[PDB]
Image 1 (cartoon, chains in turn cyan, purple):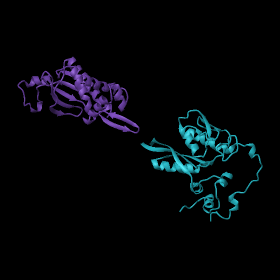
Image 2 (tube, chains in turn purple, yellow):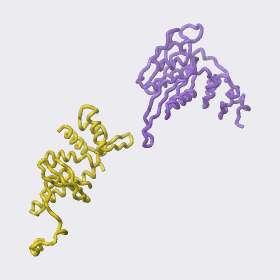
Image 3 (cartoon, one colour):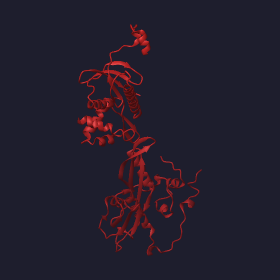
Image 4 (cartoon, chains in turn orange, brown):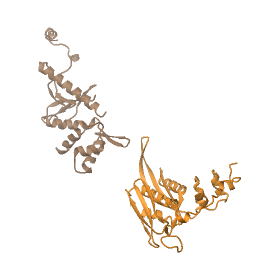
Length: 217
Length: 182
């Protein structure tokens, strides 16, 4: 049994929040991966890289392991986590955890018409990390993912079906590339379109409707 | 010739830096493959001619007193000296004295000097050179003294002399001339 320590966490444990769309709606900082695990039960991780790094720690040459892990729904919820640890499997597990924490949604949209489900993205987007820039362009239906297999796998863990990609910079260093692609798919909920010009009233948080609950006793 | 020449090369691969790593003994030798260098260093270490200092992220090779004198023997192969080694007469403080023999068969005296990494070797070298020059000064002035053959960098090889100390000498017949002499 998991006990929370945060009042977001004991809201999530109380069954008072159903989806993460409240948390995504209210820009909340998450600090409990159990929230992500209880709200994304069909969240499927995948390791991207495990690599031994040789440390020099207080006259000791040792071997730790850098694990770059991506978690991701088959719908539009992605997460990236990079972790160095003394063991392989501990680095795997804590990289999974860090990817559970940094889950962001995506806005996958249409190309051209308005039929069925959104398959491609909704606009062009761009992410940068290091010198790696990744540019995402919408694609017609059934065109696959034109991307390098790391980036392609990070997009397959998003439910992005159709996208053209172009990069620039030294894309050899794959963690800069995955971070830049992660920024590019995070910025899709960041570009204001005319179909979202409609003024909306500000809804209240769960922090005050459920303020009498979930307080530290 | 060749193995002694490469051992002279790693002897000359000592007067470059401090405690010498593995790839410098790989490359100063300039030999063909991993075979000759690594199996030579292992033959050194198993005969205690070299030692391993592993200071963090840094392999290095520590020469003890053992794997030097061969080169001196090679240095004395150059200068017509000793072929057979070993008969202990006298273990002194700053030298160990042995009775040896040449290819010619005459017995000689081998004073090895042990006075690490550079300074034991180098101070034995300075001691041997200083004593060789003092012997040269005594023989140049004309003092009756043993004749030096060579000073193989830190091991002095000289002649043997048929003498016995005066504590076991009762007297001679010409005592006042011996007093005038002394």
